Every structure is written in C-alpha cells, then in structure tokens.
Amino acid sequence: VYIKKVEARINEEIERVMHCLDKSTEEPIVKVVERELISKHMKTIVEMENSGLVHMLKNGKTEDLGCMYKLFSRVPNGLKTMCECMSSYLREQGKALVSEEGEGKNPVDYIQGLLDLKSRFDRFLLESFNNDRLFKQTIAGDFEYFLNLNSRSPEYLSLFIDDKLKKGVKGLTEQEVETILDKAMVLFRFMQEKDVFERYYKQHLARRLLTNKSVSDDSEKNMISKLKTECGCQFTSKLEGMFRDMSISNTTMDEFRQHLQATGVSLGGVDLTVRVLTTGYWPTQSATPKCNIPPAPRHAFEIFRRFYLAKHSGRQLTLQHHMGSADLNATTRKHILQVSTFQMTILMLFNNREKYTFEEIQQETDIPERELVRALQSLACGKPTQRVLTKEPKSKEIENGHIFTVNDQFTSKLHRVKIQTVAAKQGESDPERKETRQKVDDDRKHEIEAAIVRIMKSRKKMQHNVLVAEVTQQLKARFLPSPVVIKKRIEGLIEREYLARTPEDRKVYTYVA
Amino acid sequence: KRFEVKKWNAVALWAWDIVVDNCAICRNHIMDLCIECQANQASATSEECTVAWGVCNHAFHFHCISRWLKTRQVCPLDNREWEFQKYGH
Ligand SMILES: [Zn+2]
Ligand SMILES: [Zn+2]
Ligand SMILES: [Zn+2]
C-alpha cells in the first residue's frame, strides 16, 4: 500500500503544481518529495519485509515488482538498492539449492529446480524490469558467484543433458526440447570450469554412442551447433572427431560385412558388429585388460584381426573387454539374453562345465580385480526376480566357495530380455572422481603450457608478473587462473635454453626456437 | 549347448606406427625418458616429461614432438599436420 499511496501523492502533486501553483517550479517539487521520501524509505524497505521485496519474490506478485520498478526509476541509486537485495535473496536460494547435504539427491531434479528458479527470475525480470541491463548483469554475476561452488556442478549439468539427450520421452515434440536446451545452455553460460564440463560431456558421448544406437539421430547436430555457438571452436573440434569416428566405423561395419561374406570358414562369425575407433579421441576406460574370449568370439576376433592385418596393414589391434555388448541366445522357449562383454567369459566357462565358484573363475581365467568383482555382483547380487545366475549361499557379501546355478524366470514377456545392471543411479564414487580430477588437472597443466608456447613466441617478454596476466586473461573463460600452479609450472621449462625465462636473467628472453 | 552366442559387438581400437617401446623422434623408449631428459629423474620437474598422442594416433615424448614443432610441424611418420588431442597413454 505504500507504493500505491506514494504514487497517488506523486500524481496529486503533479496536478497541484500544474494548476494552483506555477508549472515552472515542477523541478524542485520533484526534488524535495522524491529525494526525501524515496531515499529515506529506500533504507526502511531494504530493511523490512511483511509483503516486502524478499517476500514478493517468493510469493510472485509481479504487479508489485513492476510498480516498484516504475517508481524507483526516478530516485537515484534506487535500482542499486533493489539489485543488492534481490541478489542477496538469489544467493540465499542458490546456496540453499547447491547444498551438498542429503547425499543421494536426484541430479536431474536438482538442475530442473535450478532451471525453474532461473526461469522465474528471468520472467520476472522481463515483465517488471523490461530487460534492464543493470538487473541482467547483477543476476549474471550472481549466477557466476555460487555456480563455481561444488566440485560437481558441471558434472551434474552433463548428467542432466545426458538424461535429456538419451531419449525425448518427456516432450515428444521439438519446441519444448528446443526451449529446454536453450535454457540449459543459458544456465551453462553463467558457469566456470568448462574443462571438467567438456570432459564429462565427452564421457557421456562415449557412453551414449558405444551403447544401443538410435537414441535421437538428429539432436546431435543441434548439440554440436549450440556448442559451436556457446563455447567456440576449441573442443567442438574433438567433438567432430568423435562423431566422425562413429559414422566411419559404421561404414567399416558394412565393409567388414562384405569381407566376412568373402570367406565364412568357422561358425563363429554368425552375426558380428565390430567398431573401429582411435585412441586419439577415445581414452582407455580403466586398464584395457586381457581376459579370455569364448570360442565363437575367439574365431570372430581372429577373422577380424586377420582381415585388418591383411587388407589394412600398417596398424595392429588391441583386445579389451571393458566395452560393448552381446546377445546370448538361451533356451519352454528360446529367450535371448544380453551380456555387456563382462559376463561372456563366466557364462562360457559355465557352458563348458557348470558348478563353478570364485576360485574356478579366478584361477583358469586370468581375470582382473575391480571389474571381475563388479560383474560377479551385477549377476548374483542385488538382482530382482529375473535372476539368470543364482547361488546356494544367499548372502550380500561375496564369498569364495559358492556354487553358481541358473533359474528359468519366465517373467520375461519377450524373447529379448537384457540385464541392465550397469549405468545405475549416479553415485560418482571417490576413486573415479579422484582419477578424473587428476586427469583434468594434467589436462590443464598441459593446456597452459601449450597456450604459453603458442602465444609468447609472438609477444614481448615479462620481468616479474607481466605475461602471467595475459596468460590468465586468455584462460579466463576456461577455468580458474591457479596462480601457484602456473608459477610453479612456468619455472620448470628452464631446464634447457628454449624460452629459458630465467628468474636471474628476466631482462631478455630468448626469442628463438 | 545351453547358452549360444548369436551377436557380438566388440569395439576394436587401433594404433598406427606408435611402436609401443620406442619414440620415432629421439629413439629411446615408450618410457626411459627422452634424449632431452637423459635419466628418469635428472630434474624432470615431478615427471612432467610425458607421452604425446596425435590425431594420426602416433605417439612420441611430449618434449620430442614439442621441439619438432619449433622446426617442422607436419608429423614425421605420414604427412598430416598433426594435432594435440589425447595425452599420457
Ligand atoms: Zn622421444
Ligand atoms: Zn624430456
Ligand atoms: Zn602421424
């Protein structure tokens, strides 16, 4: 009611000075009223509530926001006094949202709530502030403030975009998909530490392309275009790298189909789907192990290797198990199972001889450690009533002398039943987080050196801290400057004369190669 | 039999003339450091002297190809201009 009554006072003073008084004196009247009333009460409202700014923001009465916007536009520094309070409220809501307490929260719901609050803030801005520059820059700085927190905010953003890209079940049409993608990239705009974002986005690309295909088949172009328009052509290049690898390996699959129709020797190449990728784009998963191979897959891999060494000489292939899938035709009907290159060896050993245990699969298999235990658990532990590998010693923890059996489980209402125990709820355990953090740290340590050796060859020399400001400004939109790290790393290249940058001879650097 | 494999979908990675066990620029080893490092340590700044991986999928000591970019810039084992994508191993 204060805004309405002060607006009525302003209007009545306007007509009073226009009729009874001289209209030439309009200036000092605005002066006194406006100045005293609004400036003194600016403090009292920044200080109050009871249906005040911080209360109307959470209630959502947009008319009051528009009224106070059109009122405080005349008083000087009023826009600042409201920007500071709305930024305080937004920072409170942010630190309440980005809170790390309550482990096990759904990240897609977290980013959904973040998008909802930023959308309501932006709509209140466009309807009340009329796309004002000051409010826009204040909310931009606010977003840049608390989004840097969490060692997992870009990771959660990547998980959200992966959940949204894997299948468009929610919002089958394209319009809402486009809007949600625009809102997602807008939210990403006010985010720092893009290196971990790109790393996790590439990991999600590898996870979504090395699995069942036909996810969207069209949204990849939109994604790469938004990446080109948002971050720029620097990682989108590796992105094209990956996609090219993909389509080229599809052509290679048709080529190998032709070359297999060329021989047909053993009953091991019935139905083969081999993918050829490069290490320059696709990194090692954990260790690239060397486990055994079932006999028909043995013959298939032998045929493929012979072909790749005969007609594609100049390069040799490496065998691994931590990637891919398969379709295990079981057999009252013939239900085909699914194994993701992990249970093939154990099931083959069971086919050769049943009634095995942990010792049998750890002695005559040359099996690794982590992934072995992982697949064992995926097959006998934490299973719903679709168990394909049962045991007599029913227990949570894994023993040694436990016999394995098989159950029918007719609950599968089809012939293609898959066991998708992998890609469960996003846990992000400590070992994988630590190893990917070390990987991205080494990536940053190599990128800073690449940038310095690419830039300082055509620039001037520094005395103490001159070129470090430039090398940090060039990496301002990438990640934090990390002064201690860059200072420790610039002094390591002094081992040879190339760009000595000696702390003793800082007068003239060697402008040679 | 009780379980018979019908389909398979392995993905086969490939390596060019990386020669796992030797660098084509300095000829030392995939490890054992480089010619511009001599001993494993010998002031290697916390072992920053690592392997560099090109898009052409060849591999050299980071140092040996870096210094090869102050003279040439087209990867000595083919002709491709050569990029700096994957690192380590
Ligand atoms: Zn070398
Ligand atoms: Zn070296
Ligand atoms: Zn090459």
Image: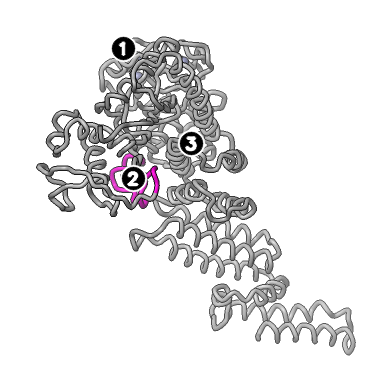
Q: Which residue is mark 3?
A: A468
User: Which residue occupies 77% across, 79% down?
Assistant: A30
Q: Are marks 1 and 2 in contact (CB under 8 Å)?
A: no
Residue marked by disc 2: A419
User: How far is the residue under mark 1 from the one under mark 2?
Assistant: 47 Å
Chain identifier of the residue bearing label 2 in the image: A
First in sequence: mark 2 vs mark 3:
2
Q: Could you give the CA–CA distance between mark 3 and mark 1, rounded to whole angstroms?
A: 34 Å
Rendered location of residue A151, percent (x, y): 39, 50
User: Which residue position holds label 1?
Assistant: B28
Magenta range is A414-436
Secondary structure at badge 2 equals loop
Q: Give the residue at x 79% y 79%.
A: A28
Chain for disc number 3:
A
Dot 1 beta carbon under 8 Å from ligand 1: yes
* Residue A20 vs residue A356, the one in the foreground: A356
Amino acid at the residue labelled 2:
Ile
Say what amino acid the circle numbered 1 marks: Asn
The structure residue drawn at horizontal position 34% and vertical position 48%, both measured from the top left corner, is A428
Which picture quadrant has residue A487? top left
Q: For this view, does A150 lie left or right of residue A376?
A: right
